[PDB]
Amino acid sequence: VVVRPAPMESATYSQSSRLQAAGLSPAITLFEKAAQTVPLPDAPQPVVIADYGVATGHNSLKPMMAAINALRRRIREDRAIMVAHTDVPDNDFTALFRTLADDPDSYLHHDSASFASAVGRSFYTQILPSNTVSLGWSSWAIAWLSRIPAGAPELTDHVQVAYSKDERARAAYAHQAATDWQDFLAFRGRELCPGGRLVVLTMALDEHGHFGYRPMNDALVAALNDQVRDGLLRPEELRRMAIPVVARAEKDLRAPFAPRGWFEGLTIEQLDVFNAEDRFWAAFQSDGDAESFGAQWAGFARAALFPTLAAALDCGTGDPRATAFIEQLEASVADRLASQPEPMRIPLASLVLAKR
Amino acid sequence: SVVVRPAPMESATYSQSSRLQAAGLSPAITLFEKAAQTVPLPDAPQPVVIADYGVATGHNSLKPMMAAINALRRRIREDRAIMVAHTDVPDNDFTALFRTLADDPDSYLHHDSASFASAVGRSFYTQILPSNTVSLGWSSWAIAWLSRIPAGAPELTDHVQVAYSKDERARAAYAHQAATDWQDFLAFRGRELCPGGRLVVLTMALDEHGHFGYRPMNDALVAALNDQVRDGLLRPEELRRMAIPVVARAEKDLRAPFAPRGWFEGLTIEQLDVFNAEDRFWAAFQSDGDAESFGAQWAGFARAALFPTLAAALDCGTGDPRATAFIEQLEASVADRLASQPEPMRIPLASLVLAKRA
Ligand SMILES: Nc1ncnc2c1ncn2[C@@H]1O[C@H](CSCC[C@H](N)C(=O)O)[C@@H](O)[C@H]1O
Ligand SMILES: Nc1ncnc2c1ncn2[C@@H]1O[C@H](CSCC[C@H](N)C(=O)O)[C@@H](O)[C@H]1O
Ligand SMILES: CCCCCCC[C@H](O)CC(=O)O
Ligand SMILES: CCCCCCC[C@H](O)CC(=O)O
C-alpha cells in the first residue's frame, strides 16, 4: 500500500540522459577534489566508492573515473578499488553490468584493479556496512521521494507538486522530502568511513523558490489532457498520475544540520545552488532545428518520468497499451515544445558532506 | 559475439522449480557451516565477505548463507558487518534476487541485522572480487555450466547433453572446455579468498562408473524435441543448433589441476565426496502414486534450468511469444512422457572443500 516511483526506462535512459550528464558536470570536479584529499583506509584494504542511484550506469562512468584516477595517484596500482552502484530492486541491473562491460569509458577497462558490485535496496535505509565508504556519489536520485506520501491528495496537475495549487499536497510532499533527506543522511553517515566524503547533486528550488522546467510542465500536462480528450486515457487513470519528484531549497538542505551544523556525524563542507546551462536551448539557437529541440526534451522526460506515469494505468506496465501510451505521450510533448522553443530553468544543488 | 554462451535460469520459475537442487546441496551446507567456524576474518572495519558464485534468483542461497552467518555470530560481535556477494552472469535477473532477499522470510537480511547483500554480474571465469577479501566462498550447481560452446566443436546430434553423444570429437571438445573452465574458476577464487579462506563447491559429477545420470530425463527431452520438429513446432535447423553446455566431472577431473603434489594456484582440496542425491520426486511417487505430480516436478526442474538455453537456439527472439510457447509445450511433453512411466534417476554430485594456503 506504500506507492513508490518507477525506475528509469532501461531501454532509453543511457541515450536520453544528456541533460542530467551536463547538469552534474560541476559536481564531478568536487568529487575529484574530494578523492584527492579524503583520508584513506589502511593499506591494503580496498577503497570503496558508493554510487547512490545508478540507473543504467551511463552517467556514473565520468564521476567514477575521475575519483579512481585521483586515488591512483595516492595508492599502489595493485590496490583494489570497489565501486558499489546502488538503486531500487526493480532497476535494470543487467543494463548496468552491460554498460560496465561494453562501454569503452567504463572504469573496468581503464583500471585493472577496480571492481563493480550492485545493491538493489532503497537508499532510504542502510545498505552498506558501517564505516566502509571512503567516497560517496549521488546525482539526480534523492529528488525521488521514497513514496507518494500517505494521505496526500491526488495531484490535479499530476506531474509536479511544485505547480499544484493544493496547499495540503505541497506540505505533504515537503514533509516527505524532509524525512527522506534526514534518512538519507543518517544512513550515509553510518556507511562513510570517518573523514569520508559524500557528493550530492539534486534538484533545487532557485533563489526565488522556483522549480523550473515550466514549458516542460505545461507541455506534459497538456499532452496528458489531450489523451483523455481523445479517449485514449481514462479520467480515473489520469487522476491517479503523480510524479513524486521534489526539489529542495537551500534551507531544506540545511534543515537536518542547523543550528550547530552537524547531523549524525555529518556536516556540510560545501554547498552550491546554481542553474544548469540549458544545452537543448543552446543547440536550438545554433542550428534552428525545432524538431530536434522537441525530441531532446521529450526523450529526457520519457526515460525519467514516463514509467512512473505509466504505472498509474489500469493495465500492467508490460502491456502493449502502456508502450503505446509512452510513445504517444513522448510524440505529443515533442510537438508542443518544438512548436514554440523556449529556454528552461534547471536549478540544481551540489553538496560536499564530510563525516567526523 | 562469436562466443556462444549458455542462458541464465528462467527467473519466473526457478524459485519454484529448484527443489531438486536444494535437496542435492544439503550435504554441502554442513561443510560450509563447519568452514565458517574457523576461517580467518579480515581486519576492521572490513566486513566479513561471503561469496556466492552462481546465485540465480537467490532462493537456494538462503539456507547456506544463514548457516555460515549463524556460525560467524558464535565467533564475533552482533554488530560486525557481514557482506554476502551474490554473483552471476550479467543477464541473470538480479531484480528477482533482490526481491527474494527482501521478501522471503528465510532471507538472512530478516534474521541478521548486520548482514548486507550485493550482486556481481560478471562471469566467474574471471576475477570478480578484490584479491584476498573473501573468507568463505560457496558455489552450488553453477560450475557445471561451460563458459561457452567450445569453439569448432561439432553440433550435438542429441543436443541436450554431451555425455550421451556418440561423437568422439564433441566429447573431447566439451571435456577440454570443462577442464580449462575449472582451472580458471580455481585460479580466480584462489586470488579472491583470503589466506586460510575456504571455498565449498557442489557440482554435477560422473558417478563411480563414469555415468552422467538423469537417463529417463535425457530420453524424454530428446523424444519431446523430436516431437516438436515432427509436429512443425520446431525447425530441424533450430534443433540442430540446440546444445546445453552442462558438463559433469569425475573425481579425476576435479583433482586434475592439483595432481600430483596437491596444490593449484595456492588452493588445495581439503575434502571431496562423490554421491548420488536421493531422488525425492521418485520417493514422493512411491509414497503417493501421483504420476502427474511426478512428471510435473521433473519437467519443471528441466524447464527452469535448461529450456532458456534451448530457447536461445530459436530463430525468433527470446522475448517472442513463440519462445514462450516452445518452453510451455516442451515442459508439457516431458511431463507427460515421464508421468507415463515413472522411474528413479541417478543424480551424481560432487561436494568439495577447497582451502587457500595460510
Ligand atoms: N529510494 C531509492 N533508492 C535507490 N535508488 C533510487 C531511489 N529512488 C530513486 N532512485 C534512483 O535514482 C535514479 C535517478 S536517475 C539518475 C541516474 C544517474 N545517477 C544520473 O546522474 O544520471 C533512478 O535509477 C532511480 O531508480
Ligand atoms: N560463468 C558463469 N558466471 C556466473 N554465473 C554462472 C556462470 N555460468 C552459469 N552461471 C549461473 O549458475 C546458476 C546455475 S543455477 C544454481 C543456482 C543456485 N546456486 C542453486 O544451487 O540452486 C545460474 O544462475 C547461471 O546463470
Ligand atoms: C515538470 C517535471 C519535470 C521534472 C524533471 C525531473 C528530472 C529527473 O529528476 C531526472 C532523473 O531522475 O534522472
Ligand atoms: C540429461 C540432461 C539433464 C541435465 C540437468 C542439469 C541440471 C542443472 O545443472 C541444474 C542447474 O543448473 O541449476
Image (spheres, coloured by chain):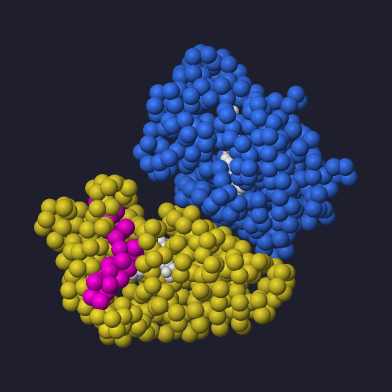
Chain colours: A yellow, B blue
How many labels, in total?
0
Q: Is residue B25 magenta?
A: no
Looking at the image, can residue A196 be seen? no
Instruction: Please tell me which residue is depicted at 22% across the width and 80% down the height of the picture.
Output: A342
Q: Main secondary structure of the magenta part?
A: helix
Instruction: Please tell me which residue is depicted at 71% across the width and 41% down the height of the picture.
Output: B176
Which of the two residues, B35 or B53, is positioned nearer the viewer here? B53
User: In the figure, A341 relative to A123: above or below?
Assistant: below
- Across and down, in percent, residue B323 comes to 41, 37
Instruction: Please tell me which residue is depicted at 22% across the width and 67% down the height of the picture.
Output: A333
Q: Is residue A306 magenta?
A: yes
Looking at the image, can residue B302 be seen? yes
- Across and down, in percent, residue A261 comes to 47, 82
- Across and down, in percent, residue B270 comes to 81, 42
User: In the figure, B294 relative to B181: above or below?
Assistant: above
Q: Is residue A240 left or right of residue A203?
A: left
Which of the two residues, B326 or A165, is positioned nearer the viewer here? B326
Q: Is residue B316 left or right of residue B18?
A: left
**Quarter of the image where one finds residue B131:** bottom right
User: In the figure, A69 relative to B338: above or below?
Assistant: below
User: Which quadrant of the picture is home to ligand 1?
Assistant: bottom left
Q: Residue furthest right?
A: B261
Q: Residue furthest left?
A: A229
Instruction: Please tell me which residue is depicted at 18% across the width and 77% down the height of the picture.
Output: A340
The magenta segment is A289-313
The quarter of the image holding the C terminus of chain B is bottom right
- Across and down, in percent, residue B158 comes to 57, 28
**Quarter of the image where one finds residue B188:** bottom right
Which of the two residues, B70 or B295, is positioned nearer the viewer here? B295
